Image (cartoon, rainbow, N blue to C red; front, side):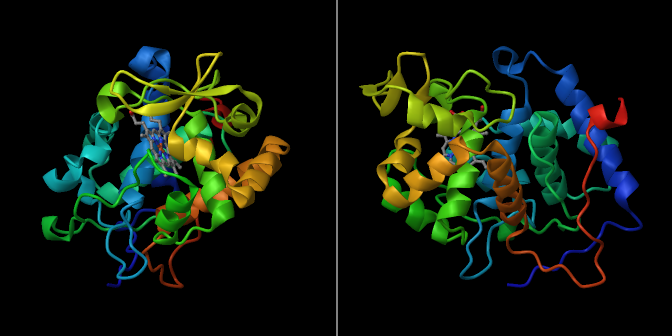
Length: 291
Ligand code: HEM
């Protein structure tokens, strides 16, 4: 399967910076969502789940085709709760009907991270919508109730290595688990709509307790009111993972730099970019624009 990036006709940096600003302006406006967390965390989760279907072996799945717009992927049990990120973006797609679905879902994730004061993420245009029959089947996204060997093995399919996996998981400092979506409940920290390295700090400094929640699932709970998933706590159980966790709890700039590279790579897996294709765009935030 080859998927070649095709820039939307005649579009350039300024067009996509207009779509960025539209998403970012609505993130500021619709602030009440999920008890004032706002839409940013569900939008970086949506960009991860449309990319996380990729399989390196046959180049199926991935962010290129925008296939989450089809019922099979929209109704995947693993995507429960992401309909709220879709409905947030649907106004903006009506306003810029020329951007492809893959591009709009991935730029929403980029915009949310930078607007929640994360690192800049280089983003590239050119994903092309593909037919309903290209939609990957349910079951390619990871279970939460498993251990470190499962996480390592699952992420080899998206060929991410240990460092990349640990840098990507730092995004679980954002938002929260919702019992009616996943059977898990609670936030992982106090700053859950500002991008920081707090996931790593909480993992190493809190007093975790294995408890059973109302959906009868086990999760790691702390006195402070935070929770960690079994696959999250996995990172301090494995010796290779645990020493990268310590590296990111001791250096927030290295965390930001490595997250930026692994999230771009995540979003680009499966796509062939021609050598005459434009460079990756670095978008300015509303704040850097005085907007
Ligand atoms: C083995 C890996 C992973 C598993 C099992 C997993 C699982 C989960 C689960 C069960 C939730 C709760 C969903 C809900 O109830 O609403 C969640 C939320 C979230 N995850 Fe993951 N995740 C994984 C990796 C990642 C990665 C790599 C990213 C992003 C780079 C990510 C970003 C998020 C975000 C931002 C949320 C919060 C959503 C919200 O607030 O609504 N996840 N994760």
